[PDB]
Image 1 (cartoon, each protein chain N blue to C red):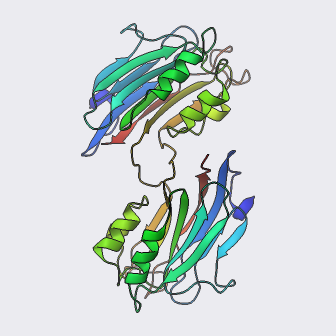
Image 2: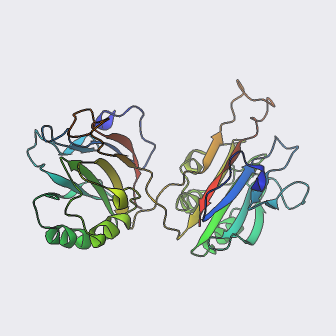
Image 3: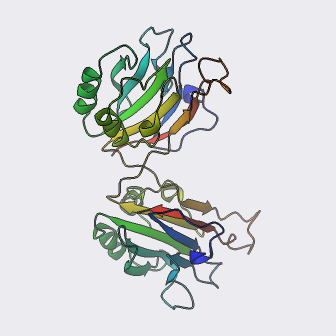
Length: 169
Length: 171
């Protein structure tokens, strides 16, 4: 399968596989639609947050950048986050450390992209995230049982499908 | 617990419990915040897709409708889907059959609400879904491991965090 994933993605969906760095030795890896976007082999990764911007319609790479969140300036990273346009898939991966230079503004911008963990990201924590700006997210509340004569509880119809959960206010 | 759920819901969350119909005999059931929105007992369910519109801020019911996707017209259902306003929680449940009369336009509109299974919904399949329009949901693709010197795989740094999935294509 594309990117080396376990199951084939449904129609009109982009396959992805990503990993954070291993200490300060092995760089992170970002792969989308069987194309390696960022990696140590590609030599386009570095210490801090490694970001890949992808076109939400075609699946093609827009830009790949890395910002040193230990020994670098947060200002060009905040500027890069603000330039992100609507309909862009945002893939982020840490290498060594991606939290020391983070500000409230930087954490707020990443949280707006769909991140829950960025507000609690600390020194040397490993983190992988795939969000976006102006991208419709699929619901985690969905259950579907196919009409299959082989296994149908009522023969002509399948069994009742049940679901319970908590919808965020 | 609210709706008769197994575990209590956390703060700023609406509790829900829903079930599809049982063949062409027992109607579907939709419950939100211990209030029965749609059921056979309430007599507001029928063959096809049973939809309950809920205010995303208060948790109160806006409207409940059912559209016959076997012997009915798809046009009033498409019109109903287009009238859904921003900040509305959409709960959908099948009864008997909810796919025969579905068109590409009807499947696209439901997919826009956060549905993955609507594109492959076939004759007499049972389906339950809880999505919404104009509600900002946090990403399902996120993995995070804290740096803890006592449990760290590399002592100074934690283990590699890996992730894989499927991003929905826009348009």
